[PDB]
Image: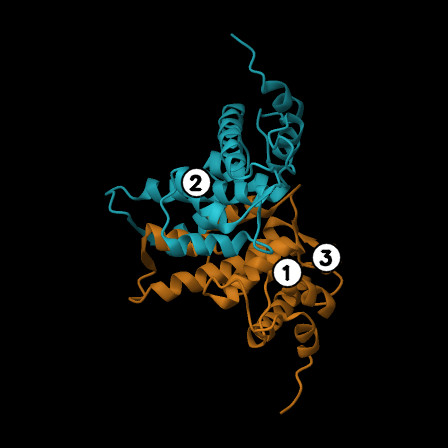
Chain colours: A orange, B cyan
Amino acid sequence: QTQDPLYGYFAAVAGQDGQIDADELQRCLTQSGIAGGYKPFNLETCRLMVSMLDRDMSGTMGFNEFKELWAVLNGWRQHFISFDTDRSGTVDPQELQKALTTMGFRLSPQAVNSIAKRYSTNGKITFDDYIACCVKLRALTDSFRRRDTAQQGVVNFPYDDFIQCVMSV
Amino acid sequence: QTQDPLYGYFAAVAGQDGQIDADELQRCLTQSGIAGGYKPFNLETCRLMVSMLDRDMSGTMGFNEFKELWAVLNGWRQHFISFDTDRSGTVDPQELQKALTTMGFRLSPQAVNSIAKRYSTNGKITFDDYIACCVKLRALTDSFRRRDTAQQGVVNFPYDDFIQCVMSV
């Protein structure tokens, strides 16, 4: 069995059960350099990542999930860079719209406006907020799709299931 | 017409249109001392507050909304203090459950677990995360109730409306 190059970072912070929480993910994401020159992800953003991958509200994730996370974040960063050619670490609401669309998110104009207002300061969205945005979008889209068993694009949400689901991200 | 004691803090940071964004709210919340000894609210948490009150994704709020916000946060802080008598600035998942229940949130046990995992580090929830939790809970509960026109406790969410709504908080 081949050694995976991500394993050292993970093994150095995992608990006794072979899992990591948000705090430990924060550390191994920073050591592993996934942000590649941009500001490293804060604890809050790492909590969102944990929920996106564990999809079970344990607050922890295993190595296989860490590897999947790492590949997803690597691709999102490359995508961001194609809009941030000068590497400012920011992007504007027009660039954000086009960035979200091209990565497979299907969003009405007012959905995009909701998102721009949510994450912009001074007409700009940081790399870190862009990633947080993508993590939460993918987690919520996975949650919605999971529940849309009839594939109608509409989900019937009981209140407590809605709260459970949306408060995890 | 009587002067309101909150107006000075608001007027010092409002834009030309008489509204404030999250950044300006952050400043006037800190100057106004609403956190009362606990750590002042960060920008992200102030973004959630703006969405809770404006309920329209403009990213801004007026003075009347600021006043309502201030009263809501004052009551939540008092409520927190009744569980944080020694004023550690933290609370544990058992205290959090009872705190949420007594302030009128109706949450199943697994909804509460979702929330504890989402905000706890080392078995503790900070005052600032408690407030963020309450802001998001009230905003999402308002969003759900608004849409539950038949009062069945179930809402039919189209995907883009779901995303719009949940990405604002």
> Tag 3 or tag 1, which sits nearer the N-term?
1
Front residue of A97 and B29? B29
Q: Secondary structure at mark 2?
A: helix
Which label lies toward us, 1 or 3? 1
Residue A10, image x and y in percent?
Answer: 66, 73
Residue A21, image x and y in percent?
Answer: 59, 64
User: Does the image show residue A33?
Assistant: yes
Q: Secondary structure at mark 3?
A: loop
Q: Is residue B66 above or below residue A71?
A: above
Chain of the residue where label 3 is placed in the rendered structure: A
Residue type highlighted by circle 3: Lys
The quadrant in which the N terminus of chain A is found is: bottom right
> Which residue is the site of mark 1?
A23
Residue B147, image x and y in percent?
Answer: 32, 43
Which label lies toward us, 1 or 2? 1
Residue type highlighted by circle 1: Asp
> Which residue is the site of mark 3?
A39
Cα separation, mark 1 vs mark 2, equals: 27 Å
User: Does the image show residue B58?
Assistant: no
Cα separation, mark 2 vs mark 3, equals: 32 Å
Cα separation, mark 1 vs mark 3, equals: 16 Å
Chain of the residue where label 2 is placed in the rendered structure: B
| Label 2 crowd bin: few (<14), some (14–19), many (20+), radius 10 Å | some
